[PDB]
Amino acid sequence: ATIGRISTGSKSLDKLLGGGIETQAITEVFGEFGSGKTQLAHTLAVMVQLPPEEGGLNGSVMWIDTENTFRPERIREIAQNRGLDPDEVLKHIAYARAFNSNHQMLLVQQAEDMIKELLNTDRPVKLLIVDSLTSHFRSEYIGRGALAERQQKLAKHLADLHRLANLYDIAVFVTNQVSATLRVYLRKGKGGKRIARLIDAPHLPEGEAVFSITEKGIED
Ligand SMILES: Oc1cccc2ccccc12
Image (cartoon, rainbow, N blue to C red; front, side, top):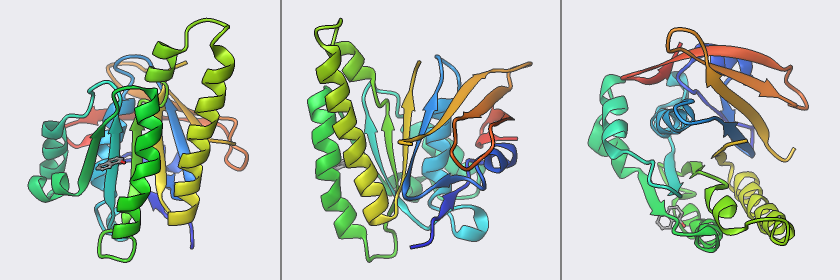
């Protein structure tokens, strides 16, 4: 199927990304605390539910949360400020807490069931979020005696995510802290604005986009 794109809410950021985040791809967003990466995740979980003319893909969402950063009230706020029904928007985000790295990998394997169920419906899964990709791996695999297994497991986890993205035409969006993925780095700009820098994209030029965080989530 043709690659679909989900608007981030920011015209500047969308332009940097070639139109928005892509289905059949893993977009990996890095940032320190308060960078805006989780705000971006929340915004995407709303935007994807819009029709294409409004920057979405008429899709449902699946969200894997590793350190309790999902905020249903923030979803409701973004939904309402963008004219959507906050209750309907929340209903179409399937939520799962991942308690550890094994569980996180299991949840990705098990997500395929719901993806299959929704595939030929009015609201197929179009966005799968993992926030954060690495918190559990960093917590569990300490030192150099553990690095090899950590990388192996992470590599397998990324492969599972790539497969879901490609097979079912889903945009996978993961957060991280410092191919295979499209890497975007967030930092604080001036006056409370945030800056995104695209790095090492095979077919998009590097560049930067400045954006804001509002009651609409993110926008220019
Ligand atoms: O495997 C999953 C991943 C993300 C969300 C889920 C929600 C319900 C059941 C399973 C889920």
